Amino acid sequence: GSMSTSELKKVVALYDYMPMNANDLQLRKGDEYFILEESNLPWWRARDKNGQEGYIPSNYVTEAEDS
């Protein structure tokens, strides 16, 4: 409904994945990012720790933190 902060959290990174042209986000292994979308596809539009947004394969990333 409103306030995206409700259903929106961060995610971790499993394998490495550098950008190709500009869309893709520079992921890595052990690092985590910030999710801004959640479309019906594995690739989202999340940003890393550099104020930059790109794509993040759902399978490649997981939960930003795990207790």
Image (cartoon, grey):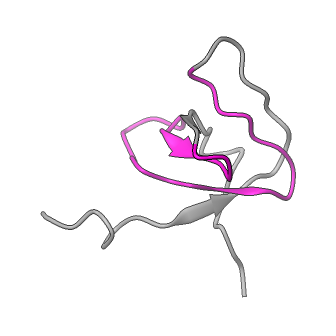
Tell me if 16 is positioned left or right of 51 in this view. right
Whole-percent x and y of residue 33? Answer: 64, 54
Whole-percent x and y of residue 39? Answer: 36, 40
Taking the spot 12% from the left edge, 63% from the top edge, the residue there is 1
**Quadrant of the frame with the C terminus:** bottom right
Tell me if 44 is positioned left or right of 61 in this view. left
Check if residue 40 falls in the magenta segment: yes
Looking at the image, residue 5 lies above or below residue 59: below
Residue lying at the far top of the rendered structure: 21
Magenta stretch, residue numbers: 23-51
Residue 25, quarter of picture? top right
Taking the spot 87% from the left edge, 50% from the top edge, the residue there is 29
Frontmost residue, 47 versus 62: 47
Taking the spot 56% from the left edge, 33% from the top edge, the residue there is 54
Taking the spot 14% from the left edge, 65% from the top edge, the residue there is 2
Whole-percent x and y of residue 24? Answer: 63, 25
Looking at the image, residue 67 lies above or below residue 24: below
Check if residue 29 falls in the magenta segment: yes
Whole-percent x and y of residue 23? Answer: 56, 22
